[PDB]
Length: 49
Length: 115
Length: 49
Length: 49
Ligand SMILES: *[C@@H]1O[C@H](CO)[C@@H](O[C@@H]2O[C@H](CO)[C@@H](O[C@@H]3O[C@H](CO)[C@@H](O)[C@H](O)[C@@H]3O)[C@H](O)[C@H]2NC(C)=O)[C@H](O)[C@H]1NC(C)=O
Ligand SMILES: *[C@@H]1O[C@H](CO)[C@@H](O[C@@H]2O[C@H](CO)[C@@H](O)[C@H](O)[C@H]2NC(C)=O)[C@H](O)[C@H]1NC(C)=O
Ligand SMILES: *[C@@H]1O[C@H](CO)[C@@H](O[C@@H]2O[C@H](CO)[C@@H](O)[C@H](O)[C@H]2NC(C)=O)[C@H](O)[C@H]1NC(C)=O
Ligand SMILES: *[C@@H]1O[C@H](CO)[C@@H](O[C@@H]2O[C@H](CO)[C@@H](O)[C@H](O)[C@H]2NC(C)=O)[C@H](O)[C@H]1NC(C)=O
Ligand SMILES: *[C@@H]1O[C@H](CO)[C@@H](O)[C@H](O)[C@H]1NC(C)=O
Ligand SMILES: *[C@@H]1O[C@H](CO)[C@@H](O)[C@H](O)[C@H]1NC(C)=O
Image: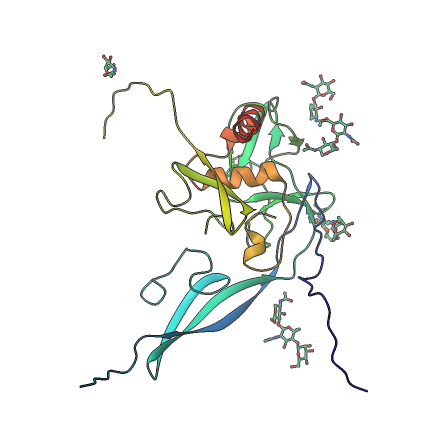
């Protein structure tokens, strides 16, 4: 069956980092990413008498 | 700033390290395509701030010191590429008695085997 | 630009040479703490090109 | 982590080692911090207090 439910929103998932005074992490291989962005520039020219 | 050059401002021309950007036109607007760079496939290493040779302290010129359990290397910060420590990628300043965490190793000099 | 990175724009994240920045929340607003670097105790020298 | 968590996965690094990275970004060599660590820490604590 289906229904409508109400709850309290969550913010994310815990990602506790392993911190010490002697350890470092270095990446080894890479990816290329392409994203998009949209921006309005103008509107319509109207005139009223 | 994004199309006619390369930007250093964070999160301005996309999310990541900026490489390029391309424009396109839309009715009453513009569209930008941002091309960036993302790291991946991290690993684990042990680090030290300096290396104490005989009475001298050596600091890395452009990279960082790492270890794989038994041997020490110097690598660049954004990509894993280990190289043998020499006198051409380190510089000397002082003696190994003031730095906290200085370790022992040897530094290879690329002149003695020549003569 | 100040919290997620290190800035080179002059007088953007505080007065001096930017090092770090920390956020705090306030009723209907935000507060930034900027940590910078200031020189001191100058001297005198003779220079040549 | 530093500034690595704003442009991808988070990578850990000791704080005194990150302070040298941030010192290199303003024109001062990184051997200055390692030989004045206690004084810099005391100044930071006094300034934030
Ligand atoms: C860095 O990441 C890239 C991808 O983002 C890795 O390239 C990928 O490597 C795998 C393993 O060699 C390739 O899989 C191959 O697929 C063929 C079928 O097409 C299969 O017959 C092979 O046995 C193998 O599984 C994959 O195609 C390749 N991706 C691309 C786009 O070429 C790369 O290996 C990573 N670097 C390191 C050092 O792992
Ligand atoms: C850490 O890296 C070093 C790289 O020198 C490894 O030592 C080499 O291992 C290969 C493969 O067994 C040998 O052919 C070389 O002779 C070794 N080098 C020397 C100087 O003897 C070492 O095995 C690595 N350690 C771990 C735990 O992976
Ligand atoms: C990393 O942290 C550890 C734990 O605080 C430090 O280990 C101690 O170092 C002191 C010397 O400063 C020794 O007297 C202790 O016996 C060590 N504790 C151990 C081995 O359990 C370590 O020095 C720190 N590393 C750096 C570079 O500061
Ligand atoms: C690095 O090597 C040096 C010399 O091989 C060590 O310095 C000696 O340390 C021992 C005990 O730590 C002292 O009894 C000697 O007097 C020291 N020698 C000199 C000439 O001062 C040093 O301890 C080594 N590094 C570490 C972390 O143990
Ligand atoms: C990296 O840290 C230590 C050192 O190798 C290792 O035991 C650990 O499993 C690795 N991963 C994480 C998340 O700490
Ligand atoms: C620095 O300039 C000269 C050169 O040493 C010296 O006589 C003078 O007192 C110093 N201070 C100032 C403010 O000029």
